[PDB]
Each structure stands twice: as C-alpha cells, then as structure tokens.
Image 1 (cartoon, rainbow, N blue to C red):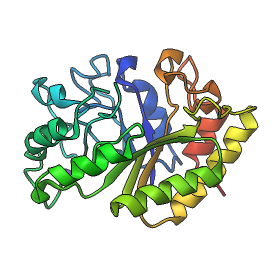
Image 2: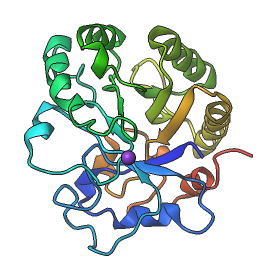
Image 3: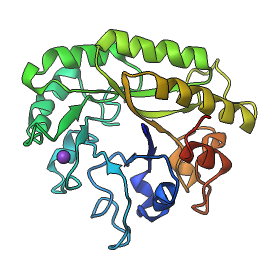
Length: 254
Ligand SMILES: [K+]
C-alpha cells in the first residue's frame, strides 16, 4: 500500500508508532522529519524496537548535513529540506540549490537510492526556481508535497497542479483536513474528517502518479499538531490509536 505514518521526533521515542504496523495494518512506511528512527535523533526509542516498514529519512535543513548523525541504514528514498520557503529553515532557491549538491552526494548507490525534492509550505515559484538551479545529474526522482485543504475538489485540483507544474511522480508527505487560509474554516465535526480521509485516500490509491502518501496527525503531545485541528489525530495523548487512526491504518477507504 501507498499509506505511511509521520511521527514528530519531539516525542523522543519511536516506540508508540510500532502499533500502527501490527497484525493486519495496511501501512507500508514511516518518516519523522529526520535521518533515523532509532539513534541520537530519537534517543529514547527502545534499543530492541522493531518497526516492520520502510523508513524514509529526511535532510530537514542545510544544518542537518553537518549534525554528525547517520541516515537509517538501507534507506531507499531520501527527502529534501522541509518547507525551506517558510520564515523549516528559510533559504533562497540558490542557497538551497548549493546545499543540494552536497545532499545529493548521499546518493552513493544510485541503483538502490533515490532523491525526493524539498517540500514547500506553499511557494510553488520557490520550488520551480530551485529545480532550475540544481545540476541535472542531482535532479530528484520524486516531488515531495505538503497539501493542507478542507474539500476534496480543492485537494484534487492542487494535487493536479503539482503534477502538471513539475511533471514528477509524487510523495505526499503531509496532508489532513485543515486550511492555513484564514477565510477557510477547519472541520466542523469529527465525521467530516472521516469523510475527507475516505475520499482523499481512494483518489490517492487510484492515481498512478501518487507513489506514497502520509496523513499528518500521529502525535501524543498536542504541541506537535502545530495548530492542526485535533480532529485530524491518528493517536491520542496517551499513545493509543484513535478511530481516525483505525480507519487510516486499515486502508482509509473501502
Ligand atoms: K536502499
């Protein structure tokens, strides 16, 4: 399946997400905005924790390349900088393109490793300029996308814009039922979020240029929602899977 889990490294331990990949789960991957899920970057994770799923590391910002920590061994995909367009660690497209040359060196085994673009918060021009400035031999295979909207029609139009603008297959690393437009109201009730997840996951499973996707909302601490509506939660304050989490983990849609 295409469906993954995001987990904030602010939680300090990867243990709580093991239960998303238990008997019957349809979820196939996970990421955490950083290099590894067991190690100094998630330092409280139990030594013996096993997560039977693909981990996708991220180079969060230019500084992460110099942090002296290692990428999760055996990675297949590497994600570029998180929301470098936001004032995320803010860079110009040229500052990002220069650091990209150093990041792209991590692809030492190019038959079994592929690079994914930086994901912008919103600035499509930022990403167009970035991709035009990097050397062609470093061009990412996949586009990373963050899409926060509240209606299925708007979701599909924006996904189609990213596909049409950039012409790469897509890894949707962050989505849920939330608009950062302030004239756009957040979900009215919990049911609307179940409905949104059903519609979006069916469309994403049926669209061949969607390689992977990842709902935003597996967290324990409310702080780690970053003002996302708590109706988007896949996990509660105690580390237990919510009804929305159950829907997601068992395939999102019939
Ligand atoms: K690999």
